[PDB]
Amino acid sequence: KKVVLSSFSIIGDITQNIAKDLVTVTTLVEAGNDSHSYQVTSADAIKIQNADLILCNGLHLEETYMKYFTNLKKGTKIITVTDGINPIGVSEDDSEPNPHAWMSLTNAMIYIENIRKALTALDPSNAKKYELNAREYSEKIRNSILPLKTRIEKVDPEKRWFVTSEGCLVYLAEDFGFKSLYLWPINSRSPSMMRHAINQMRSHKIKFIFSESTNSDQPAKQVAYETNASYGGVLYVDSLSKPDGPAPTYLDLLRFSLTKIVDTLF
Ligand SMILES: [Zn+2]
Image (cartoon, helix red, strand yellow):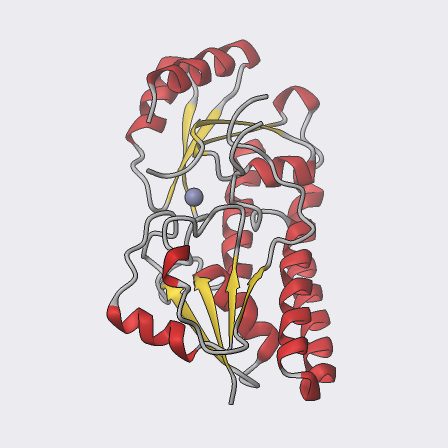
């Protein structure tokens, strides 16, 4: 039985829905651990050696721990599951890529397709099962998320802003046709970015700013105070929640976070 290692919980869960126990799906950065800054342990090194296929986000998500993906089993490839996704930079222009491509309905389909493709090349005798599984999961995501997009698209053009702490929604904004404002591009910053967000929120009359499940809510609340806006609450973006939490799957993560976003716009 083949072993497929996903770099973090979001990719692991997507892969599980496509493979459905045809392969063993493992995860490097488990839910609750930090996808942007991870220390690979000795036990993790065993997962890496056992991997017949390694599934990474790319867009530099794994840059600080890519060095551990060495001395690999012969034939084991590292697949970048964001292939075909136009990067969005961390600056406001050339700059490093923002890694959070999975916060997008469109990109969900691309993650799924790339994983289907890689699983099929790894395990070609199960091609028909991966094909079926990938379509079913794609439809499942679409059925849950599209009604949220439909509500979101009713927002008036003046209020088309996602304001967050980390720049975690830049791909969602591009996907749905919103503008995004944030305090720092990637979780572990700067006074000027905070000042810029405060001025932009006042200039555009923005009413809400969120924080997220793995960072502090204090900067968002301070910005809310200084802008006469409201704190929007906590979104899930960088990790699945614990199993008894609100976002224990990728589908649930998208559904929860987008629901919470719509429920502040209306
Ligand atoms: Zn992040």
